[PDB]
Image (cartoon, rainbow over all chains, first blue to last red; front, side, top):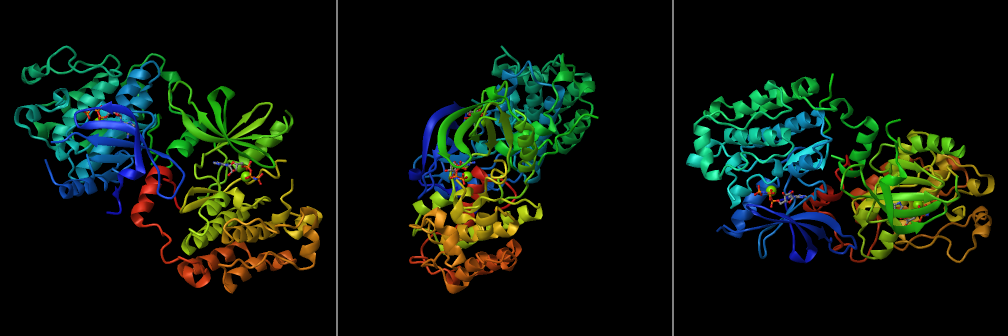
Amino acid sequence: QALLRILKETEFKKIKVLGSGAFGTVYKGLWIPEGEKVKIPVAIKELREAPKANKEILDEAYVMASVDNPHVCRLLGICLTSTVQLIMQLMPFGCLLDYVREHKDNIGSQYLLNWCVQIAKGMNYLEDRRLVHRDLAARNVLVKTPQHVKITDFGLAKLLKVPIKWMALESILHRIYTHQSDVWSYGVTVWELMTFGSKPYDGIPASEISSILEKGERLPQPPICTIDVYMIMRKCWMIDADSRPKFRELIIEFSKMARDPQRYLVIQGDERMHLPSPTDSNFYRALMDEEMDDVVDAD
Amino acid sequence: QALLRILKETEFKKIKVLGSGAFGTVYKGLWIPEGEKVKIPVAIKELREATPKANKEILDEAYVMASVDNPHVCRLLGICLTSTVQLIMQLMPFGCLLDYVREHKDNIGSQYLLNWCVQIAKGMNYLEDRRLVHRDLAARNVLVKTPQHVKITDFGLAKLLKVPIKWMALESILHRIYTHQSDVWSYGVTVWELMTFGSKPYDGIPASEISSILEKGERLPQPPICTIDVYMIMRKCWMIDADSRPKFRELIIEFSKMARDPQRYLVIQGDERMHLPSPTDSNFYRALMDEEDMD
Ligand SMILES: Nc1ncnc2c1ncn2[C@@H]1O[C@H](COP(=O)(O)OP(=O)(O)NP(=O)(O)O)[C@@H](O)[C@H]1O
Ligand SMILES: Nc1ncnc2c1ncn2[C@@H]1O[C@H](COP(=O)(O)OP(=O)(O)NP(=O)(O)O)[C@@H](O)[C@H]1O
Ligand SMILES: [Mg+2]
Ligand SMILES: [Mg+2]
């Protein structure tokens, strides 16, 4: 229980709504430690309801509180008095989807491929712990710093707007959720990144997706992607789940590609869009990211 | 070196005054990374007296200040060189340990007090290892990162430039001699400040007369909560002969020993209840505020 702090409603306040999704509402909030005069910013996710006893939710939460990996967001605290309110670290940069749309004119290959590496690393860790995400998407990758992203919202789908356009075929047709169906979503997430945040299958209703998948139709090749990168996405969307890549294979392949990033993505002005200098990296870490490094560098 | 970031004045803004000291104003500020929309809270120390040529010498010392790497010493992160030199460091919303002990007066337990003494000694020992003399150690110059993790600040500022007479070793008052052993003296005063929950040292005695009473052998008095064993360490910090003062490495051992049996060495009313930090509350503080290597 040492990893999950139980909060009294009297020691935190919700300030502003940050967003809403299939599972609840995320607020920017404050934590006021008892006996202290500081207000510490936190993120608070207030859950919709689905129903289940407080003890069973607490059991679920201890598992979410126990993930230990630089690319997965850990549940920090919980309040079960009224609604279910989860407390986690506030990520001022927001989610990676909004970030890639915001900076579509300034994202280099080194950033894009290193994000693919980090997302695969967080997902491989989840597979190690036998935790199926069920809702991996670019909106559920949080930006700690532009050089450090983290998967969030895993297993909320367990504890309780169905993301049809990210689900593997077997998940749509038969509600089968495995680590290999997470690999399908990972492939859509990579597609979101490489298109700088396009909406997948835009204009196609969700009810049609299973049918266009069965006809063999897939998301198109992003204009910056060489075939090498596009083949990885295709493999994530094979009908046979065991034929799809493994998260650990994805880590290796994207890490390789990150060592020669301009050979695998075609970006105008890429030469001027490198990872930060050592000076700027040291400054970011000291202010926002004291916890991993391991960014893969060119050459 | 890559450990000091040179900032552009357009990159940050001042949003609140936090206090002032002998060398400048400390502000709460906001850092806006270029081309981002986020506002990242920082602390800024604007120095007093407008500086040019000096700026080379300031930088050379800034690079040293930016090279300190220890969980109990604050590292300079960046610098802005305008008509006023502006230093950028991590913001510490709890503030300094002096105000902290005052506001929680007679509500702090012995385990905290003794652990702060260890941590400060570890930080000063690291500086002595680096051959760096602080010159202005005092409880006001220890910041609280979390109640479990304190850090020495303002290393290097004094050299970078009213004298804190009541924290200074006698030889520093008389001869402007500053060594690691004079830092030991100031450490003893800092500890006395903590153990008295933030009392002013030599209250009622003018600063110009401190050196006379020190030479007569007068010293700060024994705090009510301190047993003989704790007070003797403090007294040994204030020996006239600098080389018979404790070394910071010995202070680490002695305070580490006492912090394993805190109630034997500090006698505080209500120590039974106080509040030590559960693993649960400790993990929560670290995840929100303190992800660095130790405390
Ligand atoms: N810890 C956090 N810090 C900062 N922003 C966050 C945090 N968690 C979530 N957000 C933002 O708040 C929004 C709301 O999240 P959420 O309610 O999970 O919806 P979603 O993730 O966008 N879609 P869904 O997949 O249906 O949950 C997210 O899109 C994030 O951009
Ligand atoms: N990084 C920081 N975060 C938060 N508060 C800080 C920080 N650095 C300094 N302060 C506070 O800012 C105020 C001014 O500090 P400062 O100018 O250093 O004067 P001082 O520490 O009180 N005396 P002195 O340092 O000997 O000149 C004090 O209340 C400090 O606690
Ligand atoms: Mg979400
Ligand atoms: Mg100071």
